[PDB]
Length: 164
Ligand SMILES: O=C(NO)C1(CS(=O)(=O)c2ccc(Oc3ccc(Cl)cc3)cc2)CCOCC1
Ligand SMILES: [Ca+2]
Ligand SMILES: [Zn+2]
Ligand SMILES: [Zn+2]
Image (cartoon, rainbow, N blue to C red; front, top):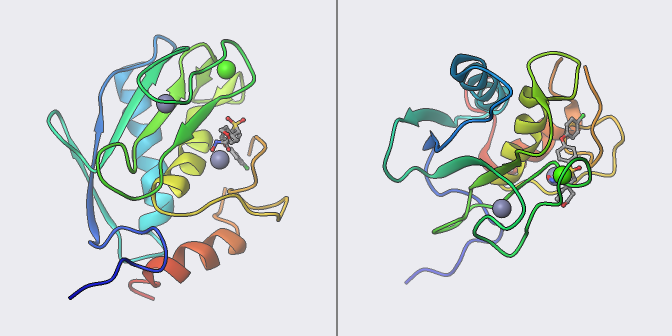
């Protein structure tokens, strides 16, 4: 027999992600690089491994949309909500949605995709918001990068340190 896990977390170390569509604001490669770096933030401190899928069903489906986009959490246009992600689980579990009414960038202008993605992926992996103002999982955007200790402690509580 098996009882459900004590916390929402993936039961495997190898996860896949798929970039369903792209934002008008950046090139495909910029977006792909931002997401790759965002995942590396977490794989670097755990035994987690991320492989990108070009199509099909991935553990973490990533998309850009506006207003009502297929869930109970519609976006709100410019500003306000920037993005949201679902904790580990079936179907939409792990999925991360970014508001395409925001101006996404690979620099300090608008909202840096790498930073917001890194925070959202924390959610996709099982982390909720932290109270520590210096944590990546703090619910308010700040532009900067080294994963704060609070986040390291949180993700390792779920998956372990991996090598080192
Ligand atoms: O946190 C969020 N999504 O994860 C919500 C806030 S949000 O959309 O403004 C948002 C999303 C991502 C953010 O990313 C960062 C958080 C901390 C830092 Cl250093 C950098 C980036 C910061 C703020 C949206 C959904 O409801 C809960 C709050
Ligand atoms: Ca918005
Ligand atoms: Zn959504
Ligand atoms: Zn958040």
